[PDB]
Image (cartoon, helix red, strand yellow):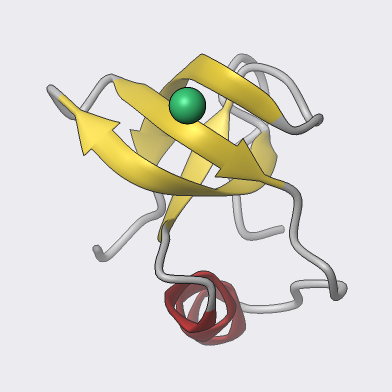
Length: 70
Ligand SMILES: [Mn+2]
């Protein structure tokens, strides 16, 4: 799993990480993401940051944490 269990369990690709706490303009990955490296590269291909967020759907703004090692 590319995100931790619990609250911040959903991988999204978000345009901006605000305050290391919020994802803005969050897109669902268009592929299965198997590893941190794939998650990072996939979100970068969409001009976005790999974040682990409180909900799994596309959204304007969500509480998120950065993917580990980023
Ligand atoms: Mn927006």
